[PDB]
Image (cartoon, rainbow, N blue to C red; front, side, top):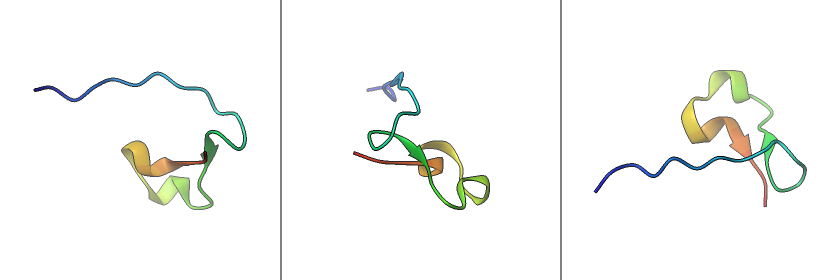
Length: 33
């Protein structure tokens, strides 16, 4: 088993930067549908 690399785009409200994305790393930087 390996970590699956997911390509995505920053498009609201599918993928957005969390308010404190700069205090967050990896997947935690992003939020959205």
